[PDB]
Image: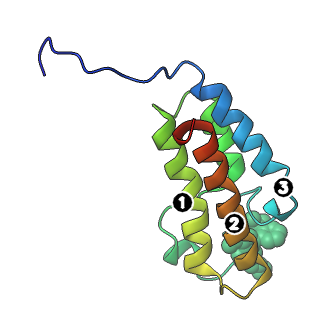
Amino acid sequence: SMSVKKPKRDDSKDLALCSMILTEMETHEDAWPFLLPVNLKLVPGYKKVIKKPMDFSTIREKLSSGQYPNLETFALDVRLVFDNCETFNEDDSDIGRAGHNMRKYFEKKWTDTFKVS
Ligand SMILES: CCCOc1ccn2c(C(C)=O)cc(-c3ccccc3S(C)(=O)=O)c2c1
C-alpha cells in the first residue's frame, strides 16, 4: 500500500529472455503453422470464430516495438496462439498436433527460465 513497498523480482533481463524463448519457438520444426497470421482470405471460419488471432510474427513485432508491458503479457499472447489452434483444429490434425507440441515446448522453457529459476 501507500509508502509500503513490496519486494519485487528483478525484471531487467525479461526482454532478452522472452526474445530468446521466441527465437527458439520460431526455429522449432513444428512452428510452421504459427510463423504468420492465419490467412483470413483463404481460411473459412477463422475470422468469425477466432476473435483474437495471434501468431509468432505478430508477437515478434510487438516485442520489438515495446508493446508488452511485462513478461506476463508476452506469455498470454504465446498461449493465445495455442488456444486458438485448439479452438480451430482437430487434435488429430497435423496442425493440431503441432500446437500441442509447441505449447509443451513453450511452457517448459517458461518454467525453466522464470518460475523454476
Ligand atoms: C486453405 C486451407 C488452410 O487452412 C488452414 C487453417 C488453419 N491454419 C493454421 C492455424 C494455426 O490454424 C495455420 C495454417 C497454415 C498452415 C500452413 C501454412 C500456412 C498456414 S497460415 C498461418 O498461412 O494460414 C493454417 C491453414
Q: CA distance from mark 2 to mark 1?
A: 13 Å
In this view, the residue in front, 46 or 89, is 89
Residue 14 place in picture, x, y as percent = 58, 28
Circle 1 SS class: helix
Tag 1 residue: 80
Q: Is residue 70 left or right of residue 15?
A: left
Residue 25 spot, x, y in % from top left = 76, 50
Residue most toward the front?
116
Q: Amino acid at mark 3?
A: His
Which residue: 73% across, 35% down?
Answer: 20
Kindly report which numbered mark, 1 or 3, lies closer to the viewer in this rendering: 3
* Residue 1 percent coordinates (x, y): 13, 22
Q: Nearer the viewer, residue 1 or 32?
A: 1
Considering the numbered disc 3 on the image, is that residue within a helix, a strand or a loop? loop
Q: Residue 28: give its label.
A: 3
| Residue that mark 2 sits on | 38
Q: Is mark 2 within 8 Å of ligand 1?
A: yes
